[PDB]
Amino acid sequence: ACEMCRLGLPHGSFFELLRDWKKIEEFRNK
Amino acid sequence: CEMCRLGLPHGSFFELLRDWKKIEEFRNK
Amino acid sequence: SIVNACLRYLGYSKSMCHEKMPIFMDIAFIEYCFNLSSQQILWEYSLISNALERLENIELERQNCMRLLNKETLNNEALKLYSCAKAGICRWMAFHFLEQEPIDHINFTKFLQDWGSHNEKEMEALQRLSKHKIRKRLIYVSQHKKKMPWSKFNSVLSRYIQCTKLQLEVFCDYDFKQ
Amino acid sequence: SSIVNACLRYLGYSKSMCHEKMPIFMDIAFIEYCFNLSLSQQILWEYSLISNALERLENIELERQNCMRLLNKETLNNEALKLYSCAKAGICRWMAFHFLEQEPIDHINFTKFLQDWGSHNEKEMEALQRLSKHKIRKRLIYVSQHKKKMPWSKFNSVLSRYIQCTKLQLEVFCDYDFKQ
Ligand SMILES: [Zn+2]
Ligand SMILES: [Zn+2]
Image (cartoon, rainbow over all chains, first blue to last red; front, side, top):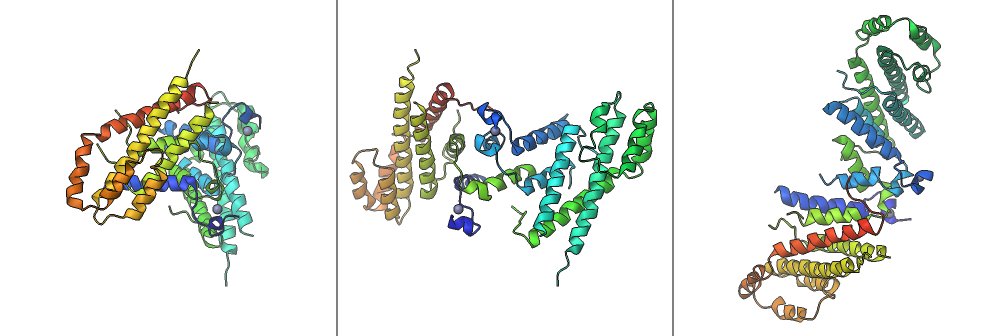
């Protein structure tokens, strides 16, 4: 009964973590 | 499951990953 | 990388022990195990039985999800490929069993537990031959491993996968690309 | 390694793990990674990112707090308190610095960030009011003499010791382990 599960969208503490993680990592890369 | 009680690794994921590292370290040597 | 923390979750956490395991994991496992990209495959009955169980899991998931357009073709193609690939894998694993001396023969005979499909000539031929003495199986296999070299089963498996993730990508809600 | 891309694909993108608890070691590792904890600033200062990081830091603080229920790791407890408060205050300080350096100043996000993370502190932040809006040139070196006042090295230290202290207390008292 979440509307992002409804919408087939990525909405997780894991998701927020990983995404933040790779914003940092592509800050690293260039 | 009686393995959660015992703090033991018992998952389809666990079997998968372990099989993964048996294959990969079979490769390495 | 620190990605292992994530791995530390999957392999080692209470909440992920008793949890559904998706099909793309079994896909990636098959592709990886058989190096789908010439035998760096690890033949040990635990490993092969597990792998065959994931293969079976993929076949069932594909089957059930498959419940103008004729994917009759994709379906029966996938059927041929699955049965011939699995029969091949069980064959080669039986071969690796035979090559070893002495033979762990009770794991052998029962190896065809789910894997030894009930077409009984493949196997009764396979096992009458259980205990003549070793050269016979070593050059029976080395007669047969230039019959149908592994390359061909690599091909069969690879198209079973490619077919499967095609059908799943199209009809059902699937994606396999990052 | 498609066999790892599969795992990340699960975590970031799967139904069963969207609405699922995130354990503390993931947030630990996230802090270690984010602030490059090791024996010097490739930290990415963005209010989304930094607020997220402070949220996981706070999450660690809470789990550490609650889980702490001959040895006297009271000492470890109060130590961890000192370290946490000084670390968080530091992170918010440097993030405020990074907000200030930019011209024009996005000050509604600035104030907001100081109303979510600057209340464990005192009211010298009203000072920030008046330096919120004097002009950039006097200010950037009104700000930049402070990293030989409070160089990042020391807050790197404080954070690293907060973490190692924390997972010490957790490893000893509670049933935690961290090595593969
Ligand atoms: Zn949802
Ligand atoms: Zn269990």
